[PDB]
Image (cartoon, rainbow, N blue to C red):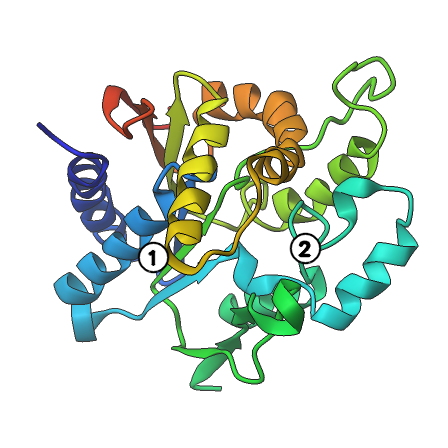
Amino acid sequence: SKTVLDYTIEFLDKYIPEWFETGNKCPLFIFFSGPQGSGKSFTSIQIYNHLMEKYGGEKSIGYASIDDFYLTHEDQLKLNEQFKNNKLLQGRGLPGTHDMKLLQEVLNTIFNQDTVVLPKYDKSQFKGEGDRCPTGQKIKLPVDIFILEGWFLGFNPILQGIENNDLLTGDMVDVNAKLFFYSDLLWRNPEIKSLGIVFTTDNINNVYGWRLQQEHELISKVGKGMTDEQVHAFVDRYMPSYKLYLNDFVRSESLGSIATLTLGIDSNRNVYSTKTRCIE
């Protein structure tokens, strides 16, 4: 049976060459989006390698996880107080906890030396609170293909009647405002041409399961991790976002400006359905 990888490679091996046949010198972005635990991270990494091997020296390939752009430990502390009463913004995690100014600059440089520098993060820092690495990564300019991945890529801010939406309340109000900067800068940015890989599942509560598994394995290995109660508390921080944006995002099939591949997977990460939308 075909895995998510099989479908993804199939989709990209058709569309990437078709993009190059256009002669476009601007970068081609490739966005990977999927709930935490869906395996989208591993899949994006596999594609990175796939492209590195296929095009190797004839094309410049870049890769980054949106979390590579988390705020410096210090700035997150600043963010904590700034939104002292918003529990969703305390600590790295939700939209608004990333360094947008830095992302803005990188994008600027890309669409502009011989290399551009992207940040790298270290989550083990400050007893697990995390901090930015003293040294990131360097990508050769111009960039031909740029792979970016995150669990909320493609989500769009609620723009109208934000006081009537029941899901959009409390701490989510600021999160929604924060989400704007990513959307505006990336998947809603008219200058960005891209292919999208979307992972969705039959039940969103699969996310709890997937993280409960991950943590149980860590504990059985080093006797340290969150209690199930804490794992629930952890995931609960992301559920509001899922409930608010996942539907429009996935149903819209437009993470990619050129084409989008949507994959539906079950608890065992098994594919039950596939769909490719090529923006008409």
Does any portion of residue 34 appear in the rendered image? no
Q: Quadrant of residue 202?
A: top left
Which residue: 59% across, 27% down? 242
**Residue 24 has which mark?**
1
- The residues tagged by marks 2 and 1 sit, at their Cα atoms, a distance apart of 37 Å
Residue 243: horizontal and vertical position, in percent? 62, 21
Quadrant of residue 258 within the rendered picture: top left
Disc 2 is placed on an element classified as loop
Foreground label between 2 and 1? 2
Residue nearer the viewer, 249 or 77: 77
The residue where tag 2 is placed is 92
Three-letter code for the amino acid on which mark 1 is drawn: Asn
Give whichever of 260, 224 is nearer the camera: 224
Circle 2 crowding by C-alpha within 10 Å: few under 14, some 14–19, many from 20: many
Which label's residue is closer to the chain start, 2 or 1? Answer: 1
Quick one: quadrant of the C terminus? Answer: top left
Taking 67 as reference, is 186 above or below it? above
Q: Determine whether, in the image, residue 280 is placed left or right of residue 10.
A: right
Whole-percent x and y of residue 182?
A: 64, 48
User: Residue at (24%, 48%) from the top-left corner?
Assistant: 16
Mark 1 burial class by Cα count in 10 Å: few <14, some 14-19, many 20+: few
Q: Is residue 40 above or below residue 251?
A: below
- Mark 1: secondary structure: loop
**Residue drawn at (40%, 38%), measured in percent from left and top?**
213
Extreme residue toward the left, this view:
1
Residue that appears at 49% across and 86% down: 113
- In the rendered view, tell whether residue 109 sits above or below residue 170: below
**Mark 2 residue type:** Arg
| Residue 256 against residue 127 in the figure, above or below | above
**x and y percent of residue 71 in the render?**
69, 64
